[PDB]
């Protein structure tokens, strides 16, 4: 299928990644840069993020979903359903509202696209209505991350997809902070894309620290596989 081929040739081996985030949460401004690489054959991403502005005013875990679905591994039988690679190289927009239960919300806009050989994710994040001593501004979330599925449906009126899911962030007392994610993606180009049957992406994420890094940062290892079509 030459449409499938185009995504294949773009993603074949290891692809370098650059992420840039400008953020404002309740007027706490911050920027983050990330670098690493992805190998969509294995659904594997390795990234390190750095707050270039000093202290990150929110927990690193609350930014993981914001900081590359084009690196998911689609099983061979599901390649007709891979919207994300289909939109490349021109790319797609990914927009979210993320509602932290009993606290504020993030609103994000990203563009994901190639800049030469490099796969880039440029993000603007605005958070509003946060509690200054709540879980997020009060830094009460554990530095870890649970596995979740992400359910994808076509958004056919918009030549795009719609994605809905819940993340449960562990809080230091043992409870959980729900982050309800609403998401929409649309192609940046005027070219055609693959519109998928309902399916999901299974995410595993592992957070660590670079023992030689003094700045405020996060090392993220993520495995992403599509499923849910036999």
Image (tube, helix red, strand yellow):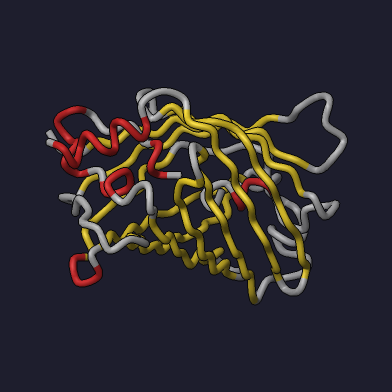
Identify the image quadrant of residue 82.
Answer: top left
Image quarter hosting the C terminus: top left
Q: Is residue 98 left or right of residue 190?
A: right
Does residue 183 lie above or below 65 as drawn?
A: below
- Number of marks in the image? 0
Query: Between 24 and 190, which is closer to the camera in this rendering?
Result: 190
- Most extreme residue toward the bottom, as rendered? 129
Residue 92: give x, y in percent of width and height. 38, 57
Residue 57: give x, y in percent of width and height. 77, 58
Query: Between 143 and 153, which is closer to the camera in this rendering?
Result: 153
Query: Between 81 and 224, which is closer to the camera in this rendering?
Result: 81
Give me the residue at 27% from left, 33% from top.
74
Give me the residue at 49% from left, 42% from top.
116
Residue 113: give x, y in percent of width and height. 45, 50
The answer to whether any part of residue 67 appears in the image is: yes
Identify the image quadrant of residue 210.
Answer: top right
Does residue 128 lie above or below 155 as drawn?
A: below
Give me the residue at 20% from left, 56% from top.
192
Q: Is residue 189 left or right of residue 76?
A: right
Image quarter hosting the N terminus: top left
The answer to whether any part of residue 221 appears in the image is: no
Give me the residue at 46% from left, 46% from top.
114
Residue 26: give x, y in percent of width and height. 72, 73
């Amino acid at each position: 299928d030459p449409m499938v081929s185009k995504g294949e040739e773009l993603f074949t081996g290891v692809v370098p990644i650059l992420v840039e985030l400008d953020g404002d949460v309740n007027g706490h401004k911050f920027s983050v840069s990330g670098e690493g690489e992805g190998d969509a054959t294995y659904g594997k991403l390795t990234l390190k993020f750095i707050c270039t502005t000093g202290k990150l005013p929110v927990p690193w875990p609350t930014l993981v979903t914001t900081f590359l679905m084009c690196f998911a591994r689609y099983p061979d039988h599901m390649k007709q359903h891979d919207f994300f690679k289909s939109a490349m190289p021109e790319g797609y927009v990914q927009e979210r509202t993320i509602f932290f239960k009993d606290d504020g919300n993030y609103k994000t806009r990203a563009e994901v696209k190639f800049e030469g050989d490099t796969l880039v994710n440029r993000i603007e994040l605005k958070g509003i209505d946060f509690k200054e001593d709540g879980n997020i501004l009060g830094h009460k979330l554990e530095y870890n991350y649970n596995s979740h599925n992400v359910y994808i449906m076509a958004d056919k009126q918009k030549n795009g997809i719609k994605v809905n899911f819940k993340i449960r962030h562990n809080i230091e007392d043992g409870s959980v902070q729900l982050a309800d994610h609403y998401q929409q993606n649309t192609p940046i180009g005027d070219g055609p894309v693959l519109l998928p049957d309902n399916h999901y992406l299974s995410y595993q994420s592992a957070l660590s620290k670079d023992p030689n890094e003094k700045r405020d940062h996060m090392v993220l290892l993520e495995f992403v596989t599509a499923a849910g079509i036999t």
